[PDB]
Image (cartoon, rainbow, N blue to C red):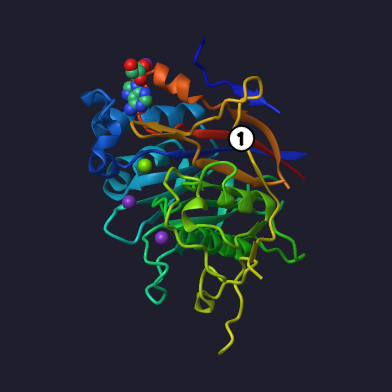
Amino acid sequence: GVIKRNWEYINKFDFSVMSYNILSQDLLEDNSHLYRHCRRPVLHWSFRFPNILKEIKHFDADVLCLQEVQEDHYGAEIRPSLESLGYHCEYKMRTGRKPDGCAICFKHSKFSLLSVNPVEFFRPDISLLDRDNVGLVLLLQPKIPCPAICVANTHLLYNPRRGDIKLTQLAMLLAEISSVAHQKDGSFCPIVMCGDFNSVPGSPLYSFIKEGKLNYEGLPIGKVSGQEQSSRGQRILSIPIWPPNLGISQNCVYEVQQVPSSNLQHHFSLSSVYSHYFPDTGIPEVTTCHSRSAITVDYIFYSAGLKLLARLSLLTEQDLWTVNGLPNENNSSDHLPLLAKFRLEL
Ligand SMILES: Nc1ncnc2c1ncn2[C@@H]1O[C@H](CO)[C@@H](O)[C@H]1O
Ligand SMILES: [K+]
Ligand SMILES: [K+]
Ligand SMILES: [K+]
Ligand SMILES: [Mg+2]
């Protein structure tokens, strides 16, 4: 019963991607009921950050996609530490009362920056989109003597009930990617989309990402994410989910608004790095474990044209409770870092 995270291995450019919700100290302390299982000393930022930095240093990924990156801590400690490791860092803070956000970092030696494309999901003119969540999309040029790579990162709305907002937020991210990744030959460049989607494998939202299609007629708003909730007394998704003045089509691309079928679509071909279930046993993988939750909500998606060489295996709920849950004295987030090795064949 050994508890280990192994590397599963499945004219080129090779690069590794890490997706990691590092847990904002402010979000930690605002929700202390989630960490009742934890010994008090392991929760302090002074304890947690060195461990998190050690992980990042150890894995030495070419691209970092981080969530719950607290602004004050980012400026003071996280960004300087990452810059020292040879990373160029781009940040997008949430737009509300919560001063955390997403960062996409990449090694100077591996890429040049073509464009930075932040996405704010908050729209003051649209009542539906009243949440502070954000995304970030970079276009990177691999440094070799080659096509660009589009890297996206997000942290979608947590609230389990509001699947209408989740899907609209996702649509806004997909729309940005569609714009940035478009090439002169009319196809999309290779895409890596990381983040905390607050949605479980096999959920409608997850299915939408994988299939590029969703029939959402008669679907309760709470069922979208597959997060734990009653589902009683929930309203059904509207057709359309979001209003025309968002300027995004049902194919999740920007469109020219004109002065004035319940199926969502996107034009990408996306695979998930992780299978979500252990092959031998069929036990589900988890990416987050605390007092109230043990689920997968973190993903690395990629265009399948990249080839996945390897991934760092996840753990079961039972495995994580053997080490008394997350965070603990050895692992300093309530999430596990996702890690993938990719190959771009030229
Ligand atoms: N919030 C929790 N959820 C699930 N299991 C827990 C929780 N807190 C402690 N445990 C574990 O459950 C068992 C309780 O005896 C122990 O193995 C302990 O680590
Ligand atoms: K929040
Ligand atoms: K409702
Ligand atoms: K235990
Ligand atoms: Mg969290």
Q: Nearer the viewer, residue 208 or 219?
A: 219
In the image, what residue occupies the spot 60% across and 63% down?
217
In the image, what residue occupies the spot 73% across and 66% down?
184
Percent position (x, y) of residue 295? 47, 35
Taking the image as four quarters, which one is ligand 1 found in? Answer: top left
Q: How many marks?
A: 1
Asked if ligand 5 lies within 8 A of label 1, the reply is no
Percent position (x, y) of residue 187? 74, 61
Percent position (x, y) of residue 333? 37, 32
| Relative horizontal placement of residue 47, taking residue 6 as reference (left or right) | left
Q: Is residue 256 above or below residue 288?
A: below
In the image, what residue occupies the spot 58% across and 51% down?
204
Q: Which residue is mark 1?
A: 274
| Relative horizontal placement of residue 301, taking residue 13 as reference (left or right) | left
The C terminus lies in quadrant: top right
Q: For residue 46, which quarter of the picture?
A: top left
In the image, what residue occupies the spot 51% across and 25% down?
315
Q: Is residue 77 above or below residue 239?
A: above
Q: Of all residues shown, which one is farthest toward the bottom?
A: 259
Label 1, secondary structure: give it: loop
Percent position (x, y) of residue 240? 56, 71
Q: Amino acid at mark 1?
A: Tyr
Residue 89 showing in the rendered view: no
Q: Is residue 234 above or below residue 27?
A: below
Mark 1 crowd level (few <14, some 14–19, many ≥20, 10 Å Cα) = many
Q: Nearer the viewer, residue 207 or 266?
A: 207
Residue 21 showing in the rendered view: yes
Q: Of all residues shown, which one is farthest toward the top?
A: 1
Q: Nearer the viewer, residue 330 or 165?
A: 165
